[PDB]
Amino acid sequence: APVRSLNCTLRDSQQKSLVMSGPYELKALHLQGQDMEQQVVFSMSFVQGEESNDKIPVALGLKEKNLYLSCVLKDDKPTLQLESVDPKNYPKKKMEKRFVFNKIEINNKLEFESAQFPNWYISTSQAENMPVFLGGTKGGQDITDFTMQFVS
């Protein structure tokens, strides 16, 4: 049938919210009160891919925008980008692999691993107002843990 999707927000484990940084990047910062309206709302689609109890393949589109997070090589490195798509054709259940993330639940937090690039994760910096990026580890000083908030 039609792919199933949920509206949501994400925050990193330092409770940094995600906002637009120009047209094709996200950044993470501490937001509270009226300024929280700047945060991006996702449509999380539940897509085709290898799946287990705590590891669920998803796509992350911007709500009612033909823009998806994707993982591609840029200057020979795995990178995170926002990518435009044909709005007639998306979302779909069989999303291309660059758009797929494995949503992993570990100790009440979520990680989003690239399905294309094993052990590369959606990441934020500890510093304020820096890009959301794809990082090659769930170790280190960058943040790879998130929580989701459900949106009407």
Image (cartoon, helix red, strand yellow):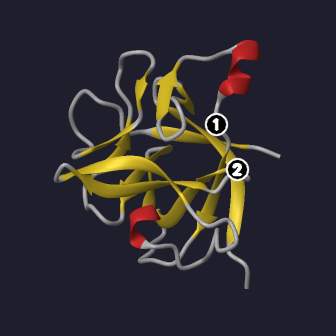
Alpha-carbon neighbours of circle 1 within 10 Å: few (<14), some, or many (≥20)? some
In the rendering, at what x and y percent does residue 7 appear?
Answer: 72, 51
- CB of mark 2 within 8 Å of CB of mark 1? yes
Residue where numbered disc 2 is placed: 63
Asked which quadrant contains residue 126, the reply is: top left
Examine the rendered structure and indicate whether residue 2 appears above or below residue 61. below
Q: Above or below — where is 78 with respect to 46? A: above
**Quadrant containing the N terminus in the rendered view:** bottom right
Q: Residue furthest right?
A: 152
The amino acid sitting under disc 1 is Val
Q: Residue at x 40, y 71 (%)?
A: 97
x 55%, y 39%: residue: 147
Tell me residue 83's x, y (percent).
Answer: 49, 54
Callout 2: 10 Å neighbours few (<14), some, many (20+)?
some
Most foreground residue, 109 or 150: 150
Residue farthest to the left, as pictured: 76
Query: In the image, what residue type sits under mark 2?
Result: Lys
Which residue in the protein does label 1 denote? 40
Task: Work out how far the residue at label 2 is from the one at label 1, CA to CA, in angstroms.
Answer: 8 Å
Q: Which mark is residue 129?
A: none
Q: Where on the picture, by quarter, is residue 38?
A: top right
Residue 4's place in the image compared with 12, above or below, is: below
- Name the residue: 36% across, 16% down: 127
| Residue 87 position in % (x across, y down) | 67, 65
Q: Is residue 139 left or right of residue 88?
A: left
Give the SS element for disc 1: loop
Q: Earlier in the sequence, mark 2 or mark 1?
A: 1
Callout 2 secondary element: loop
How many dots with numbers? 2
Q: Where residue 71 appears, x then y in whole percent?
A: 36, 56
Q: Residue at x 76, y 15 (%)?
A: 34
Horizontally, residue 25 falls left or right of residue 60, namely: left
